Each structure stands twice: as structure tokens, then as C-alpha cells.
Length: 118
Length: 118
Image: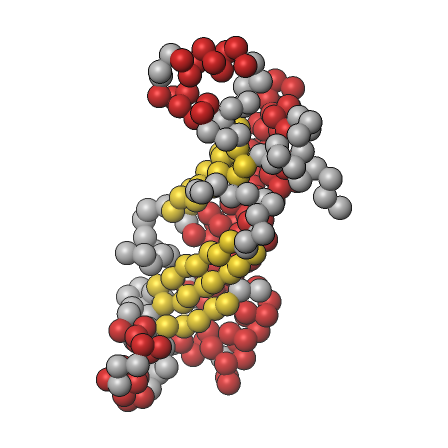
């Protein structure tokens, strides 16, 4: 119901939208740093954590033109381009595995979004 | 809103109700094993994981009499004695810390609820 059953055949899902903190770090280029050259960082990042991890929202493609054009076209896949710029973490698994994965991805992503942490 | 802000001053909360699997293990005494003598296991368990962890529902006190009496009295604190027998994990913290704690407690509790796991 609201309960987790450990013996359920369904996986659980955890999803989180973490805001990229552009307000706190107005000039830091998060989107570049996270994606990496040709998207290698976020590829690696996904591979290391076992989570699906996406940069979404206004600024996510760093091509004000292309972004404008895709929104204007009305296509629902690009609907996210209107939202605040954010990292979207999605994991699935049995409860223990899912929380572990979310925790792993959450903590790796924190490292990117709080870039002057000690 | 639905977003996590890493710089929010509010902690987040994660709560989960995990069913003790009495159906799958009809004779195994989960409640005893989890609480421990004098409640030391669950004390330790909470201390090791950093989570609040409670056994709730019918069977949680293993005193069919006392349980009956407390429910019958109508006091709202004992309302849970009607629910399926379950472990209730609650954690608070900033996102990375919260998921880490939930993950830790979830996986420790799994060890108690799937007692013949390899």
C-alpha cells in the first residue's frame, strides 16, 4: 500500500530533481563540468553510480538558439526546457539496492553542485 | 517545490514502512531478533545507522494481552497496533546525508528481514 514489501516482484523507483545552484554561483559553468567533453563525465558518472542522470531545464544545452527553437516547436519531449536548470536522478531496484544507488548518485552530484566544498 | 535545493535551510525527511515478512517466515521470531535483549539490538542498530527505527503493528510488543488492552483504550499513540507488523525507518538531513542514512538503515534492516539470505 504505502508499505514496502521486500518480496514484492516490482522494483521501486526513486526520482529527484536537484536544482543546479546558479543563484549561489552565477558565473560557474555547471553544465559544461557535469556533461564533460562529448558527455563523457556524465556517461562515467552514470556508469559509476548506476543511476540515470540528466541535465534538464533552461541552459541545459548551452545553445540559447537551439533551445529556443526546440521549445517553440511545441514537441513534448523538450517541455523541460522551461523549468529551472536541474539535475534529474532516477534509480530503480529493490528497496535496499535503490536507496543505495540514489545515495551514491546524490553524493556524487553534490560534489558537482557545491564546487567549493571542503 | 518538487525540487531539492541543496542550499535550502530545511532538512529533508525520508520515511519507509517495511513489512516484516511473517508470510514467508511463519515461525521465525523477527520481533525478538530485531529488538534484542532489553532492546539493545535496535538501540545499537539505530546508533550504527543514524536512523530512527521502530517495530510497529500487531505483534510488535509480543504480549497479545497488553497489545489488546492498549488498542481497546483508544489512545491515539497506540493506533499503530492495528497495522501489519512492520519496521518504520525515519531519517532527516540534507539530501546527500538523508539518502545515505536511509540506504544504510534499509540495508541493515534487510539483513534482519531476510534471515536466510546468502
